[PDB]
Image (tube, coloured by chain):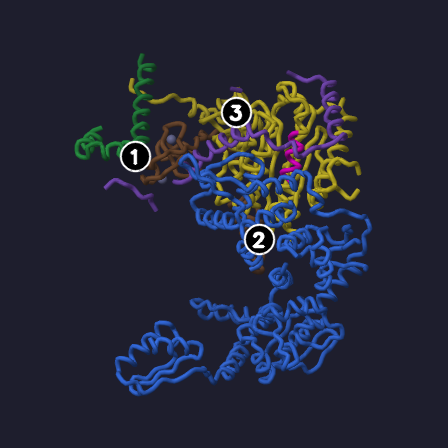
């Protein structure tokens, strides 16, 4: 959902703002890589010709088999307003945006760029020792403060404010603490590339009055920069933006020159495993991971018992699962984490069981489960235990003078989808507190 | 295998595992060298047809089935769906 | 030719044109065979 | 959908290009082709950030890899452009600088034959290396050949090209050919494109070459099945005779060496493998059609 | 079966490209003049239309006869 998320945000932006956004070649190049492969093919054809092509011609290129992909491509391009459909002389002519066409032309042909990609100071620093360590630690710190594990250096107010108001890491003053939510666990599950965009996308919505295009302009060219290089300093809004960028471990400053980091390059949709753990019948967890971040996330629903340098060993318990469920983590998410962080050995034995299953009877092909089904059943059963009681808040209706009135009132509540339960014998029905006013309003009417 | 291959005893192979069996099958794809004293040199008459691209389907002379495109024989103009095959009319490869 | 004429009158050109196209390659092939036979017969015989 | 590898086999040689300038009214047309290639490679890099580029130059006395440069710099391109683009273009132009100097020193050397076969074979080897080394990458070949120069003998070119066709087909590596020169069709290169799902294009004028490159030879391997190729010519997949040299529609081939012969070879012996045919059997072919007496 | 350049000419032409390359290189000049792009596009589509018609009709195929 990376290209979907970035693309969807661009669509919501008004066309008037999009035109100004396409001014810099850098952002146009980044936006070009987001469109579907067919869209890029048409765009490249149209960038280098200052003419008008009728719509039907582009359709002729697409084969009959790939006709479906044509509909998606044209729809995506039109929504971003990159392609301007002009109708005249009885034909629906097609043309490319003049600003976008010029922007792409300069980048490819090396025309005047107005320092969109930045400048080089020729003062490089060691990437492995400094850039990797700084961003890794800074990104590590924010993650720890999100998973709830104690950490000395808490994040700054800027990122702290962003996390709270967003769905991530819901906080309550009365509780006096911060805890993860259903979306928060998904955020942790998402790979680093999608993990970074979620925070950046939320920040883009947080900024107010700072221009929306300027923030988008800075973010796009940041990926264009190459790690381990200097870049001298930019818009006035981009200045405070650059300092705020340091809070997320994307750019490093000594105190005039800013250095992009691995995360900065990774932003622009760049193309045994650590975290693998063994889940077995005895509800014992053996995670072959050596990293506090992996340990912290595991503790959300695993009762850790001890840790070695090479791995951490723990046990799944009813208390541990309930703790995660209470916060808002769903069981389906938990199994996804277990399945996606499986040990290679588990797959082989599961495949061996499948091979024997096929040998005895090859007529059945069920989706293979890396971890034993018993763990799945118990975890889901515990979820059912927490959902044992279902309660709704609202009001009750009784003592209707006429049966027709009761039916009329009940029927309307069903129409507006606020009727929860009803009994014809007792002439009673219960409605949700949310739709209590609507039912009462209809009663008066 | 011996008397039929001019006394050579290397044409009778026994596998030792499934991996070797695939090698044995694969080795048979390559053409087998001919014997010196077994001479059968000659010239074989075959032609090179030209592919066509017609607007409407036409019956094929090999299967009597309607097919859009086919290769026209250079000796009798009959069309064949696929190659390489012996022409169904003039018996020319 | 008789089949084309039979289809022509029966279908009134609605199917004759399609019928001729389907059988065109075979009709040309047989005509070429006769043409080759006629052409060579003049040479060897005379 | 997935990264793709583009390998451009540019055939650069003063003899091929000088003849092009003399016949036409354009001087230094190699710059226009070279300039178009630089933008074309940048356009390919702009399609995706995970795609690589390779350029092989077939000079008079051999072949050389322009990009990536061997581990074993002048300013020709502005330094304000995108870093990745310049990282390739600057090396590409620099190698052209060195290659021309090397060719200039050996100008008096006798260039007996063209070396397009080696570059195409070399490109395929590079394609194989990247695919296995990195693991899930598509590949494509682009041949920029200048056919204006009157070739000496193209027969030697037939065998290497046909072998390359099979290798490209097996590896799913479509090869496209762009030809600039007098002759409209190349019986061998055009055959290569059709047999490998490639695009063959011929342009008489060097000016405005980018439009062709970006509109015809820009179909990435990811979307090849859904794009209809713009090729206009047709191929017969026929081969010339060994004695007459003409295209043979119906003829004879030796049973041992598979050498095409339009007519029965003189002396009743094969001219390629020195194999003697049976007098009776060859007489069978010589027999005339049966006609009533 | 259905002018040769002298040695000096190659050196002369090679020097011209040698000078044209070292002095400067302008990629922006690659863009057409808007008078040949229309001609280039017009002929390219001419093949597309023919190819599209050929490829739209590339077990037995459905027929119209009874
Ligand atoms: Zn057939
Ligand atoms: Zn035939
Ligand atoms: Zn022979």
Q: Which chain is brown?
A: B
**Percent position of residue A166, x then y:** 60, 68
Q: Which chain is yellow?
A: D
Whether callout 3 and callout 1 share a subunit is answered no
Q: Is residue D241 visible?
A: yes
Look at mark 2 in the image and give the residue it sits on: B23
Whether callout 3 and callout 2 share a subunit is answered no
Look at mark 3 in the image and give the residue it sits on: D241
Which of these two is toward me, A143 or A291? A143
For label 2, the crowd category at 10 Å Cα-Cα, with few meaning under 14, some 14 to 19 and many 20 or more, is few
Q: Name the tint of chain E in the rendering.
A: purple
Magenta highlight range: D32-41
Per the model, the C-alpha gap separating discs 3 and 1 is 36 Å
User: In the drawing, what numbered circle is on residue A250?
Assistant: none
Could you say whether the residue bearing mark 2 is in a helix, strand or loop? helix
Q: Which chain is green?
A: C
Q: Which chain is blue?
A: A
Which chain does tag 3 point to?
A: D
For label 1, the crowd category at 10 Å Cα-Cα, with few meaning under 14, some 14 to 19 and many 20 or more, is some
Give left or right: position of A164 versus D259.
right
Report the residue at 42% width, 76% height from top: A435
Quadrant of the rendered image containing residue A108: top right
Q: Is mark 3 within 8 Å of ligand 3?
A: no
**Percent position of residue A199, x then y:** 63, 64
Whether callout 2 and callout 1 share a subunit is answered no
Look at mark 1 in the image and give the residue it sits on: C22
């Amino acid at each position: 959902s990376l290209k979907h998320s970035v693309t969807q945000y661009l669509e919501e932006i008004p066309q008037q703002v999009q035109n100004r956004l396409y001014t810099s070649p850098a952002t146009c190049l980044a936006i070009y890589r987001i469109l579907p492969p067919l869209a890029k093919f048409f765009i490249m054809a149209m960038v280098f010709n200052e003419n008008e092509v009728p719509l039907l011609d582009l359709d002729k290129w697409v084969n009959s088999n790939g006709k479906l992909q044509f509909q998606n491509a044209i729809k995506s391009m039109k929504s971003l307003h990159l392609l301007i459909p002009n109708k005249s002389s009885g034909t629906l002519m097609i043309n490319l945006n003049p600003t976008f066409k010029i922007s792409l032309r300069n980048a490819l042909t090396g025309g005047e760029v107005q320092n969109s990609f930045g400048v080089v100071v020729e003062e490089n620093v060691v990437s492995l020792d400094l850039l990797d360590e700084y961003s890794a630690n800074k990104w590590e710190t924010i993650l720890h403060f999100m998973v709830g594990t104690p950490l000395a250096k808490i994040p700054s107010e800027k990122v702290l404010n962003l996390l709270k108001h967003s769905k991530l890491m819901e906080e309550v003053n009365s509780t006096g603490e911060f805890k993860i939510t259903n979306e928060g666990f998904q955020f942790l599950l998402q790979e680093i590339n999608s993990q970074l965009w979620t925070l950046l996308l939320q920040y883009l919505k947080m900024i107010e009055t700072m221009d929306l295009v300027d923030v988008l302009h800075f973010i796009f060219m940041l990926g264009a920069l190459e790690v381990g290089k200097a870049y001298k300093i930019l818009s006035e809004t981009q200045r405070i933006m650059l300092q705020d960028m340091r809070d997320y471990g994307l750019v490093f400053q000594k105190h005039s020159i800013f250095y992009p980091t691995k995360l900065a390059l990774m932003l622009t949709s760049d193309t045994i495993p650590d975290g693998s753990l063994i889940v077995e019948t005895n509800f014992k967890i053996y995670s072959y991971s050596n990293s506090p971040l992996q340990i912290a996330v595991l503790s959300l629903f695993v009762h850790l018992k001890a840790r070695f340098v090479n791995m951490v060993l723990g046990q799944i318990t009813r208390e541990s699962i309930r703790r995660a469920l209470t916060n808002g983590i769903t069981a389906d998410q938990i199994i996804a984490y277990l399945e996606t962080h499986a040990h290679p050995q588990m797959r082989r034995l599961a495949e061996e069981k499948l091979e024997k299953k096929l040998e005895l009877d090859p007529n059945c092909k069920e989706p293979l489960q890396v971890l034993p089904p018993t763990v799945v059943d118990q975890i889901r059963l515990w979820q059912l235990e927490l959902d044992r009681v279902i309660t709704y808040e609202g009001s009750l209706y009784s003592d209707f003078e006429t049966s027709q009135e009761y039916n009329l009132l009940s029927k309307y509540a069903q129409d507006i989808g606020v009727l929860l339960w009803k009994d014809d014998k007792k002439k009673k029905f219960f409605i949700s507190k949310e739709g209590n006013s609507q039912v009462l309003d209809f009663a008066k009417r | 295998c011996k008397a039929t291959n001019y006394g050579d005893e290397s044409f009778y192979k026994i596998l030792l595992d499934e991996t070797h069996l695939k090698e044995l099958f694969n080795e048979a794809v390559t053409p087998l060298p001919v014997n010196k004293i077994n001479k059968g040199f000659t010239l074989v008459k075959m032609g090179f047809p030209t592919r066509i691209f017609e607007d409407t389907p036409t019956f094929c002379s090999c299967h009597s089935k309607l097919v859009y495109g086919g290769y026209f024989c250079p000796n009798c103009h009959s069309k064949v769906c696929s190659l390489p095959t012996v022409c169904p009319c003039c018996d020319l490869m | 030719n008789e089949l084309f004429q039979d289809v022509l009158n029966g279908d009134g050109e609605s199917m004759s044109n399609t019928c001729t196209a389907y059988l065109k390659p075979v009709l040309n092939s047989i005509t070429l065979a006769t043409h080759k036979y006629d052409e060579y017969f003049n040479e060897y015989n005379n | 959908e997935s990264p793709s590898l583009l390998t451009v086999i540019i055939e650069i040689a003063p003899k091929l290009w000088t003849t092009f300038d003399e016949e036409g009214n354009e001087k230094g047309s190699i710059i226009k082709v070279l300039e178009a290639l630089i933008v074309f490679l940048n356009a390919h890099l702009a399609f995706n950030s995970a795609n690589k580029v390779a350029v092989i130059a077939a000079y008079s006395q051999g072949i050389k890899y322009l990009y990536p440069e061997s581990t074993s710099d002048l300013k020709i391109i502005n330094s304000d452009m995108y870093r990745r683009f310049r990282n390739v273009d600057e090396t590409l132009v620099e190698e052209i600088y060195k290659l021309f100097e090397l060719e200039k020193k050996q100008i008096e050397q006798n260039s007996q034959r063209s070396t397009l076969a080696g570059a195409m074979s070399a490109g395929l080897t590079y394609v194989n290396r990247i695919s296995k080394e990195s693991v899930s990458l598509k590949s494509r070949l682009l041949v920029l050949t200048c056919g204006s120069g009157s070739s000496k003998d193209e027969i030697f070119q037939y065998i290497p090209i046909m072998n390359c066709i099979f290798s490209a087909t097996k590896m799913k590596c479509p090869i496209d050919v762009v030809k600039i020169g007098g002759s409209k069709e190349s019986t061998f290169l055009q055959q290569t494109t059709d047999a490998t799902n490639g695009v063959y294009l011929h342009v008489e004028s060097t000016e405005g070459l980018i439009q062709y490159l970006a509109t015809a030879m820009f179909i990435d391997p990811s979307l090849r099945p859904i794009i209809v190729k713009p090729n206009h010519g047709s191929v017969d997949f026929r081969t010339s005779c060994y004695l007459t040299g003409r295209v043979v529609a119906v003829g004879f081939i030796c049973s041992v060496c598979l050498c095409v012969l339009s007519i029965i070879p003189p002396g009743n012996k094969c001219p390629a493998c020195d194999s003697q045919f049976d007098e009776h059997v060859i007489a069978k072919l010589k027999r005339k059609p049966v006609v009533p007496r | 079966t259905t002018l040769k350049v002298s040695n000096q000419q190659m050196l002369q032409q090679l020097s011209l490209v040698m000078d044209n390359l070292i002095n400067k290189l302008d990629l922006n000049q690659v863009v057409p003049n808007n008078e040949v792009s229309n001609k280039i596009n017009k002929r390219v589509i001419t093949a597309i239309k023919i190819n599209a018609k050929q490829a739209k009709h590339n077990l037995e195929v459905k027929s119209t006869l009874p």
